[PDB]
Image 1 (cartoon, rainbow, N blue to C red):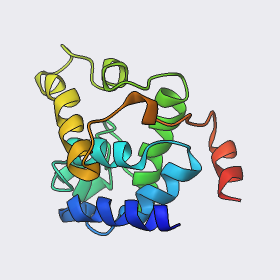
Image 2 (image 1 turned 90 degrees about the vertical axis):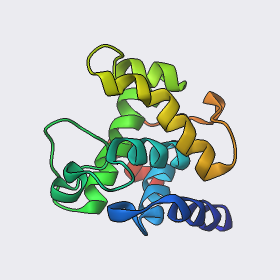
Image 3 (image 1 turned 45 degrees about the horizontal axis):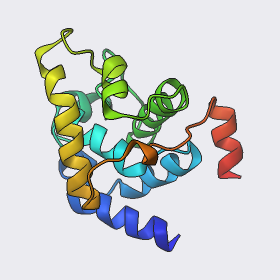
Amino acid sequence: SKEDNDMINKLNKVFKNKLSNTGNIFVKYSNAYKVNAALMAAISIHETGNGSSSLCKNKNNFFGMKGMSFGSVDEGIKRGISNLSRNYIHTGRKTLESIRDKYAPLYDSPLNKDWVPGVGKFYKQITGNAYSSNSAGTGVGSNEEAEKNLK
């Protein structure tokens, strides 16, 4: 909780625009889904131009999840962390390279070569530290397992 409050403050220091003051949402769902809150925050910043994208503003889509929209900021951030936990980090995608290979494959789109550097830059801007894949988290297999962790 002192650990959580410090991570919440570090997130909210970097978050701008529609990401502002959402540090507590990132930390809440990163804990329940057993993943790195600063990594979740770094991917959101990259995908949204730090909460400035129309996709982020109009569709509460904080993770560049193509052609999706969400009913609230909470649920949009939550859905993005759930997807990254269940379908990436829990399946064993721990490195920025192995996450990118699935998340933003190199030749699908020219912006995709900016993903590993972009996410890396923001992760170091949040924590003071270069991202280590040992930090990724275990992730969880299901929303049901995440819900059990919240209780």
